[PDB]
Image (cartoon, rainbow, N blue to C red):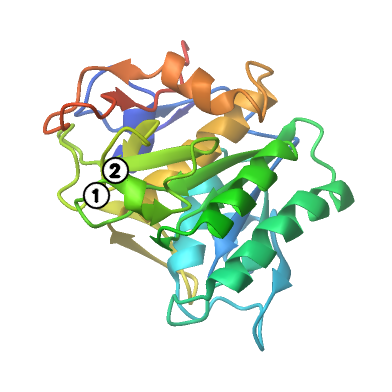
Amino acid sequence: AAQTNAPWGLARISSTSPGTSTYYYDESAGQGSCVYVIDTGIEASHPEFEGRAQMVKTYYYSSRDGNGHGTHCAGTVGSRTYGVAKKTQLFGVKVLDDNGSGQYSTIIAGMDFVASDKNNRNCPKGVVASLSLGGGYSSSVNSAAARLQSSGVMVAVAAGNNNADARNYSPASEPSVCTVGASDRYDRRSSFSNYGSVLDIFGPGTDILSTWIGGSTRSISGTSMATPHVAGLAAYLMTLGKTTAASACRYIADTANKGDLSNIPFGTVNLLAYNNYQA
């Protein structure tokens, strides 16, 4: 399948070269997979989600996304126009308040929630969790991410936006999950992207168009935007049967575009997520 005039990041993940604008992908499109977006919530009523998104958990007075961040990330995972895996099921877990903030205890609870809640959902092709959040190093936060991964969920986490080594941030620094840095449309490391040996992969993160609250759209930047590209890619590849939750990060690294990004610090992988779709 081909989506013309796609957001640049979708085109990038199906291309061996920057500078194109059509997204190519197998029509299965992540059908039968599930992606949890652990964030500020999801505006599930947005026409872009087509009834495939729902809130399953909140730790606050509402499950609604009063911020937009979680809706944007969910849109990059699986919205019809802005999403990588256009037929996946999206589940929202609101661990961040409408200012985008959350306590680590709540974030940990949300990860353990997903590890159990997947057993209440129909995801025959597999389960992914997208965590566009983080803060300073916490062994307890890393352990929660490791549990979620161990339970059979492909965990993708943002590297962080400090232009610093991600070893000092959580859950970015957890070795067993997929830590995602950000790139721009010219294949440069995004100016804010964290780096370091703990990164597994880069995805599009600068000037990413996606869904927003109020039934709208907007373009924003962050490793928060790169992470759902990788989460959606994992769901798509799992639906194709090419990989599993336990192996998808490694598979994405195996099949990435290699050596094509600029300003990658020595010691950080030079790997850009790629769906290897041959039309």
Reply above or below: 234 against 95: above
Query: Along the horizontal axis of the image, is 232 left or right of 106?
Result: left
The residue lying at 26 percent from left, 47 percent from top is 194
Q: Is residue 33 above or below residue 240?
A: below
The secondary element bearing badge 1 is classed as: loop
Farthest-out residue, right: 120
**Can I make out residue 43 in this image?**
no
Residue labelled with disc 1 = 206
- Of residues 41 and 248, the one nearer the viewer is 248
Residue appearing at x 57%, y 38% in the figure: 85
Image coords of residue 127 (percent x, y): 70, 39
Query: Could you tell me residue 243's position as x and y percent?
Result: 63, 19
Image marks 1 and 2: residues in contact by CB distance under 8 Å: yes
| Number of the label disc, if any, that sits on residue 182 | 2
Q: Residues within 10 Å of mark 1 (few under 14, many from 20)?
A: many
Q: Which secondary structure, mark 2?
A: strand
Residue 244 appears anywhere in the view? yes
